[PDB]
Image (cartoon, coloured by chain):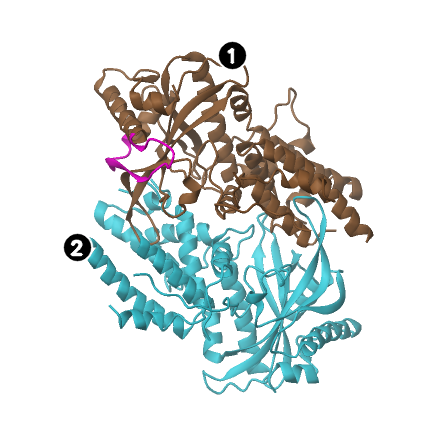
Chain colours: A brown, B cyan
Amino acid sequence: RPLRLPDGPPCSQRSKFLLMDALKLSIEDPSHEGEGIPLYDAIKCMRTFFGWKEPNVVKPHEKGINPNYLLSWKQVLAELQDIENEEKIPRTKNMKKTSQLKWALGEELRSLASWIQNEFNKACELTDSSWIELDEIGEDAAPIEHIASMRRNYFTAEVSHCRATEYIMKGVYINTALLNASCAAMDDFQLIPMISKCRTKEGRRKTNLYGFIIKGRSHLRNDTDVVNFVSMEFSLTDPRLEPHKWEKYCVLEVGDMLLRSAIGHVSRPMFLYVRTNGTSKIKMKWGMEMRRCLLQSLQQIESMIEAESSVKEKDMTKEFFENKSPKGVEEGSIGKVCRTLLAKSVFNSLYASPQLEGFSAESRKLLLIVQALRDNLLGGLYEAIEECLINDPWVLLNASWFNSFLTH
Amino acid sequence: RPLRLPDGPPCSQRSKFLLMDALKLSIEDPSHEGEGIPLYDAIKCMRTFFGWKEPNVVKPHEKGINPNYLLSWKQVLAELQDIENEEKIPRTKNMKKTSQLKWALGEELRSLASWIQNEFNKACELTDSSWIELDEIGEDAAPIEHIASMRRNYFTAEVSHCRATEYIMKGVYINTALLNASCAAMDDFQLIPMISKCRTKEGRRKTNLYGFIIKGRSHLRNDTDVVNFVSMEFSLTDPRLEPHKWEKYCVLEVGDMLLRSAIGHVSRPMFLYVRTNGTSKIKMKWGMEMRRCLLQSLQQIESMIEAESSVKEKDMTKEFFENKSPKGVEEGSIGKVCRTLLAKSVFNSLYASPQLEGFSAESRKLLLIVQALRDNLLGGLYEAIEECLINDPWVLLNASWFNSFLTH
């Protein structure tokens, strides 16, 4: 009996930042005065681009004040130009408390849509760049033993370039910046660049700018207290292709970018995805810990090597990772297994919800019952599972996956 | 005005062999007596697998004699067992001219379905293994100049592991084997293994067996003369998931395979996709030349570097491949551009048709007219294009792509 997924309008994006749709302005081997200070790096990235034009709304937010989102972007650009006019670049920039920002800062069943499976597939892919160091994974006090070290190196080599690892590092950077600003600049509408760093295939350092957030007032006395923010994220994705995805956003067209492509140089509109959002102290602390997805994925891999090693009375680390009893890998390669596990862990973090906790607990129970029936040959459990299937894209995708598992 | 795609039942697979659905039985650093002789290698690969079971039809061919396809597979397995009983393995194996083989060997609008876009996406992916040597590309008589060499090395590094390159090498091997057998064994129902070879990420030689074909009589006096064959190809793909894809096939369940996976070892049914098919001498000669897709893709890349070099009065090879004027790559990376170009070239070969030649000629004309109208601001051209849109999955996908180009 397959799970009944809800009927309704398609589900929409609810991540704290863009995933597959993100666009970076980047600088390579940066060495300007103040290299490493987020605002300085942001300005350097912004300075690489000369394609801006008069911005306009291309996908209105159905429940927001569209003119205020437009004003907010124009204010970022003007306040950055104000800095260029000053003698020195200040370490942080606090935005004028304009009417548009005061508004923006706050001072139902849905059906599964194809975009979330597509996000997940993109999260499993390899990128050109590496996102973590060779010794990134682990927190051990002492030096790791030989077999542990071997496993970490093999795993790290499969995931250091994975898109999901970019999302981890993006997530760590932005949550670190917003949590720090929430403490250090409680009354300020601080401009917070969305930054990541990577190493190119050629070995060069690269600093990336995805966009900006502006925070609101943030007197976060308890873990559950919320800081509001407005995010402004670059993209080449035309929001008119899948408008249901972008329910929570006002989308601007803000520039044009020249790109290399299969047909030679082409010019494409550059968009800016704008939304109001919020996060709590506890959520930011978890965001800061997203590197744990790597440890937890490695541990899942290590558990399987341990099982095989136990059987063959021999360490099976090399045989597992080199794919040397099994005649293949269902996902296609060991590397794809590593990345798929990682991507699931990262999406569990990015799309954390109570719907997800319930679905996860309840579905595991049903799995175990159905396997016991399958190997050897109710409602209430089903209602517990299906009550979690409301509108969350990640939970719905996972329910769709569960149903495939049942058909087979 | 978008192209009108045909209405009808979903389009079906028409490639000469399986693409994304293929499964290999493989052997590593092979060194048995007669290593390199196709039949010997096939037997070695077959010997790696102990999961066979009594075969049965799981997806019947609606217009074929299903019992004969089943008999044909059982006959392959028995004739291979006959060899194991003999003192020596013969160099080639000619099949008994049984009633099932004599039958098998011959002795309407469709709508676009999602599977062909999915095939194309899979063709663009990287694999764990390399499929070509460092000096594979090019036929030059003399040693290549420095700039040429640099470009070939950068390009080769982006495509040597590409799935599309596997399809090239698979295609070259099988067309070479069938063309050779058609000449050397004209009256025999020769068993022809479907083989490829690669090098693992660790540097080990690996020989792969995809399945078998059996040819019919082949007195190919002219280029257009046809040799019939029956193909028998391994797969983990359950044909009941997308039966419309498998219209031309009888699909058997023939074994079970133990696999590593994200959830530990799992057992999955192994299927055998069986169909009758045919090819001509001219088509096999083209199949033998599939390495030209690599040269032609490189040439497309080289043309773009030449254009940039002409502009900047400087060779732009490094700057192009290292992605150092353009601010990005529309497909995401230079590597993805290389693989996408390659995949399009490979699919043009794999899915060659008159529908494709007409669509290609006519659509290019319409592109040029629409761009001229776009930059500076009929039916008959449209009928020429749309008359090519009948049932071919590759042409239909390309028409769908053309329509996206129009919307934008």
Residue sitting nearer the eye, A267 or A154: A267
In the rendered view, would you say A115 is above or below B218? above
Q: Amino acid at mark 1?
A: Arg
Q: Position of residue B100 (x, y in %)?
A: 68, 82
In the rendered view, would you say A194 is above or below A368? above
State the residue position of label 2.
Answer: B376
Q: Secondary structure at mark 1?
A: loop
Residue sitting nearer the eye, A303 or B118: B118
Magenta run includes residue A64: yes
Q: Secondary structure at mark 2?
A: helix
- Find the distance from the CA under tag 2 to the CA under tag 1: 61 Å
Residue found at x 52% / y 30%: A133
Q: Residue furthest right?
A: A376
Residue B335, numbered circle = none
Residue B36 seen by the camera: no
Q: Which residues are magenta?
A: A47-67
Magenta run includes residue B390: no
Q: Position of residue A215 (x, y in %)?
A: 40, 21
Residue found at x 75% / y 51%: A325
Q: Residues within 10 Å of mark 2 (few under 14, many from 20)?
A: few
Q: Position of residue A204 (x, y in %)?
A: 41, 33
State the residue position of label 1.
Answer: A221
Residue B241 placement: quadrant: bottom right
Which chain's residue wears label 2? B
In the rendered view, would you say B300 is above or below B68? above
Side of B386 where B135 appears, left or right: right
Side of A351 where A253 appears, left or right: left
